[PDB]
Length: 220
Length: 231
Image (tube, rainbow over all chains, first blue to last red; front, top):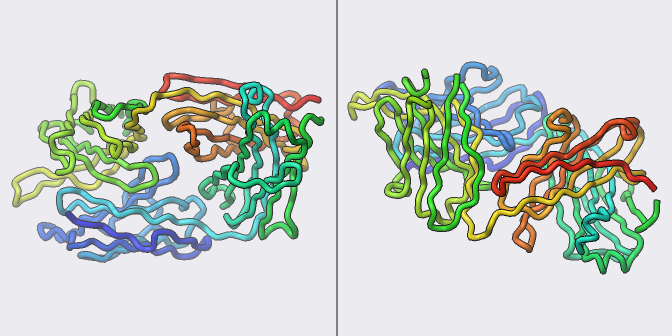
């Protein structure tokens, strides 16, 4: 079977600049009968199915912007996106259909660069409904920041927490090229009610010093 | 051209699943091929097979041959992929995809090529765990979630199994500023995620905000109102 290998696995490119993704096949995917490379490119956004961009290595599908171009022959192929736009954030895949089984490359994620954006930081105490059930989830939201690196630390009565929080980050947003992050601290009801001050401390390139959001259990 | 698949399911190891894909505007069932491709969570793609509906002939990847059947019903423009003796490793989003055919002058046959339309996908989870509905808890807007003229509020979507959930706000009327985070599988064997939205803080006393969650694997839908904190 033909192994499809993409390079790089991820890249970050500035808007209006060129993005180049490579795909190499373990053997030739040139079909002699019509002298076409049976090589296709797809774009996939999160939660969405793949969308066809290019087939026969270099023919654009109708509706696809002309900033997308494919080139290569035989075993070495390239997808070039010129004048990159925000809506081009996605994972790109190559696929061959010369040989059965049809096979795909492993994807290349494309992200975009932008200026630093500090997070807006928000905190949510657990609901009384959840506490009644025996557990407290405390949520610290870091909204719309860039770059993706951030430090997030929980303090409970000023004690740094370890091993009891969970961080989830969104994929980069097309509308403003930012990320958002949720940090959820999980405590039993009994531990939640032993302490009063709940704080999440966020450090980020866009913050001139770390930001703390906190609340006092029980207070307005 | 539209390809609509059946919903997400949990299946026990050793069982079989049948996924459907209905095409609507047929040109598709008369002149095209329909393939099935799967994508394990967090990974790439594996072709399982395809069929050319007007001929009834179907090819399959070696690794599925014997265990997979692809059929197509021209009177309902619906194609199906049945996969049997399910194993953990069969957990994936299964896609149907349409594409044109070319003729191979050496084989003397029509063959599959590129896919031009994909369906939305069907997440099939193979697990001995039972499905479980989510519980929705509010992330109430308050002084600690407001800045300038903006407030954040949200929905904690807790303790469900397996993936996926769909989360909407106000029956899909509210889409701007929404972030639904990727679920994390908890030590308990259950998933949780939050969904949040930023809105004008001036709206909080007058606009209702409801979190709508659909969990197809447990056949549950939940709606929860999220109201501002009141002291």
